[PDB]
Image (cartoon, coloured by chain):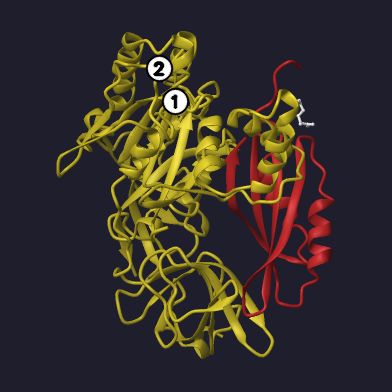
């Protein structure tokens, strides 16, 4: 098309179960999620205290194609690694 | 550089308003987000001629680079004014942003409404059913009482004074119907693309004398959008209110024990305080508090902290419970609460007995619309009828809610982050609520077992 779809950039916090959770597996499983209109971006592991680190990961979504509710629920199916997800920030593009 | 106070701003407007270029320009020239990418494109821009470049061209390339997924910085964006460090949201069009605006972290202190000046684009942006009006209504309902209007694309209407005046008139009508007082609102003619009246004053409008706003102490005037943002009035932070800390997560850490994590919403948490977790009513001492890399002597409103407590298992407290000070208005579960509900546009009508999920702070609980007590005039609160039989889009109503699971909430007047909520249904937020009253509250642990 000559005109582009509406997009948002979202930073997700993905929290582990404890300080021993395999974080590389956790982010690999997030990045394996494929949805039309979803682009994974940069990520870092960020200390939150007491030796726990959260995954902070960017993604870019086409508003009309990618439900953020659905994406969070999908990430949370990795119950062996993921305790919860939260939206750290989000912006229009 | 001097020490700054912190404020939150949300930027709203129609897809053709240019609000992303406008917000991007402020962050570029007054902040430090994705600066390595900025620097890459400033150098690349030499290719367009002999070295000169437009900020808007760099912003366009930064946007494309973000779309590729290869920029580094997260979506938490900030910039400086003389007085403030501003955390800014260029409001997404995403429909899941509505819940995030209601229950997400930090309400805005000021909304900035960006208006396209062109004739067709202006009219499109003030539609009663448009996303822009909904964002404005949500901000107003949530207590964002400060507003700035920027009339963008002034180049496209040749910086014509009459056109600006007519836009100000029509936009004043638009925002008054939402509920804002236009006399308190600066109207700034800008060009987000060319920088006019963004950080430096325009030379394209000799008629332009500046913006003004009435405040409680007098009339404040300026020329630029940056000046209007700097003139945002310092909000009061709830440092001295009693502690409220809704839980996001709870960890069991070997050698440490139970570590709840959450945002301090009101009050302050310190090692050595005795705290209570609602709705369970477990009480214990705070052993230590940590945030990011540091151990804290106190966590203050806005801090996302972990803290270690003893004699509480990870199984007796959970996400959505609320931690507060046992010594100072401790939090409690409720039997019911009454709230003013604003019904958003959605394909339905609401009768007593409706039981959707409510999101309130970190709680996610289905609550019955037990009684529809009043319908009200939205802006004034005046009661229009007792016991309406249904609610439709646009209605404001007092509703009695009964939570389906134990739930800790507060009146919005007392603890605002625990007194606003989103109602979810049909894959959208269908209503926003502001809590007006709460009906708050032994079984031994041996007896429970
Ligand atoms: N002038 C252009 O469109 C090129 C933009 C940028 N310098 C790039 O190579 O991606």
- Chain of residue at mark 2: B
How far across and how far down the image is residue A84, in percent?
Answer: 66, 62
Q: Colour of chain A?
A: red
Q: Which sits in the foreground, B439 or B216?
A: B216
Q: What residue sits 54% from the left and 75% below the top?
A: B317
In the rendered image, residue B377, in percent from the top left (x then y), is placed at 25, 32
Q: State the residue at coordinates (30%, 31%).
A: B186
Contact between marks 2 and 1 (CB within 8 A): the answer is yes
Dot placed on the residue nearer the N-terminal end, 2 or 1: 1
Q: Secondary structure at mark 1?
A: loop
Q: Quadrant of the N terminus of chain B?
A: bottom left
Q: Which chain is yellow?
A: B
- State the image quarter where residue B353 is shown: top left
**Residue A33 is at least partly visible in this image:** yes
Label 2 lies in ligand 1 vicinity (Cβ under 8 Å): no
Q: Left or right? Give the position of A13 relative to B428.
A: right
> Mark 2 = which residue?
B204
User: Which dot marks residue B196?
Assistant: 1
């Amino acid at each position: 098309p000559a005109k582009p779809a509406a997009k948002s950039i979202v930073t997700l916090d993905v929290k582990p179960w404890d300080d021993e959770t395999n974080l590389e597996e956790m982010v690999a499983n997030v990045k394996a999620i494929e949805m039309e209109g979803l682009t994974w971006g940069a990520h870092q592991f960020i200390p939150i205290g007491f030796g726990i680190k959260k995954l902070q990961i960017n993604c870019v979504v086409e508003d009309d194609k990618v439900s953020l509710d659905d994406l969070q629920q999908s990430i949370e199916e990795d119950e062996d690694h993921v305790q919860s997800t939260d939206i750290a920030a989000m912006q229009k593009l | 550089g001097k020490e700054k106070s912190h404020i939150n701003v949300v930027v709203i407007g129609h897809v053709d308003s240019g609000k992303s270029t406008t917000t991007g320009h402020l962050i570029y020239k007054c902040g430090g987000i994705d600066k390595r990418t900025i620097e890459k494109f400033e150098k690349e821009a030499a290719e367009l001629g002999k070295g000169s470049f437009k900020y808007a061209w760099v912003l366009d390339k930064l946007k494309a680079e973000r779309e590729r997924g290869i920029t580094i910085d997260i979506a938490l964006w900030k910039f400086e004014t003389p007085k403030y460090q501003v955390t800014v949201i260029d409001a997404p069009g995403h429909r899941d942003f509505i819940k995030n605006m209601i229950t997400g972290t930090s309400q805005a202190d000021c909304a900035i409404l960006i208006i396209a000046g062109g004739v067709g684009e202006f009219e499109a942006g003030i539609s009663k059913d448009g996303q822009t009006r909904e964002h404005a209504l949500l901000a107003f309902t949530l207590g964002v009482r400060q507003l700035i209007v920027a009339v963008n694309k002034m180049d496209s209407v040749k910086w014509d004074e009459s056109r600006f005046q007519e836009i100000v008139k029509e936009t004043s009508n638009f925002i008054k119907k939402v509920g804002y007082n236009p006399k308190t609102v600066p109207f700034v003619p800008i060009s987000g693309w060319n920088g006019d009246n963004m950080i430096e004053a325009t030379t394209n409008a000799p008629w332009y004398k500046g913006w003004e706003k009435e405040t409680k102490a007098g009339v404040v005037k300026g020329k630029t959008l940056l000046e209007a943002i700097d003139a945002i009035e310092q909000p009061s932070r709830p440092t001295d209110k009693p502690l409220r800390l809704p839980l996001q997560d709870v960890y069991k850490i070997g050698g440490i024990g139970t570590v709840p994590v959450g945002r301090v919403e009101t009050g302050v948490i310190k090692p050595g305080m005795v705290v209570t977790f609602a709705p369970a009513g477990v009480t214990t001492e705070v052993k230590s508090v940590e945030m990011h890399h540091e151990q804290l002597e106190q966590g203050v409103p806005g801090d996302n902290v972990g803290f270690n407590v003893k004699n509480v298992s990870v199984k007796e407290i959970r996400r959505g419970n609320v931690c507060g000070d046992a010594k100072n208005d401790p939090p409690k579960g409720c039997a019911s609460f009454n709230a003013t509900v604003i019904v958003l546009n959605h394909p339905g009508q609401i009768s007593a007995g409706y039981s959707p999920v409510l999101d309130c702070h970190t709680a996610h609980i289905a609550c019955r619309f037990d009684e529809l007590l009043e319908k009200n005039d939205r802006r004034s609160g005046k009661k229009l009828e007792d016991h309406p039989k249904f609610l439709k889009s646009g209605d404001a109503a007092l509703v009695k809610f009964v939570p389906s699971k134990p739930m800790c909430v507060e009146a919005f007047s007392e603890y605002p982050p625990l007194g606003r909520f989103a109602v979810r249904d049909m894959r959208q937020t269908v209503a926003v609520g502001v809590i007006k009253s709460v009906d708050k509250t032994x079984x031994x642990x041996x007896x429970x077992x």
